[PDB]
Image 1 (cartoon, chains in turn brown, cyan):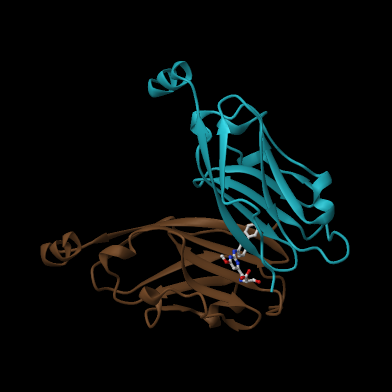
Image 2: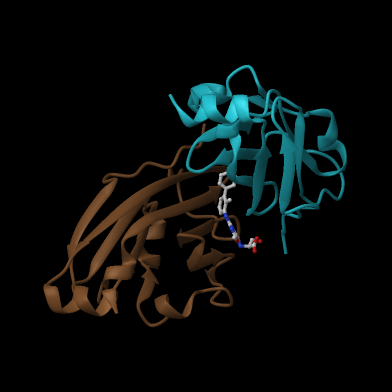
Length: 125
Length: 126
Ligand SMILES: COc1cc(CN[C@@H](CO)C(=O)O)nc(Nc2cccc(-c3ccccc3)c2C)n1
């Protein structure tokens, strides 16, 4: 059936860097964008909502606005790729990509963020 | 748009009893049973996978085998109802109902499990 595949289940990124996380779905010939549904979330916090042919930024979290973008060019090739710029300590956790394209499946990705003492002290408050 | 509806966000059930948790999805005409996908989960642990008309328990956690079943009759009016037999202290947590039927949505449900001392002390060890 329809199964989403993740090439890498764990990402290790440095503080302030940019990370692009990848999950893949099977594409037959072209993209019926009127049926593609991509939901990117981490810890019950929406990052990006792809419904119809565009993004639904009505539920995107503020912490991920101006930092999160799904590579629309890669959706043709069946790669729902989410990019987060300036990864911070709070971007560590379990991410979930849910894709609906005829079928439906989801896969989880765990992100670990290394950081220097200064940035870590900031998270400790 | 397509929205999943939960009549109850919190369940309070007794140890050893039977519990049925309900999430609801809108059906206008009939079932595209080739397009209905129902995922019942608890804390990144699959409970039930309803794809193409039947259940695919191939990813079901061992803790739920022989106890979890999706009520196929309630699918008539958009009721994806999950029943757990022998609710245990380990069955407490955040459940997730994920449905794809002409769109996609999911909602979370929290289950609290009361239990007598004997079952709790036994669960507190091992
Ligand atoms: C939390 O909100 C939203 C919103 C949306 C879409 N946005 C609109 C659509 O109409 C809205 O429903 O609001 N999809 C999602 N999850 C999602 C996305 C894709 C597939 C699946 C899925 C379904 C069955 C099995 C496995 C995965 C799921 C759960 N979650």
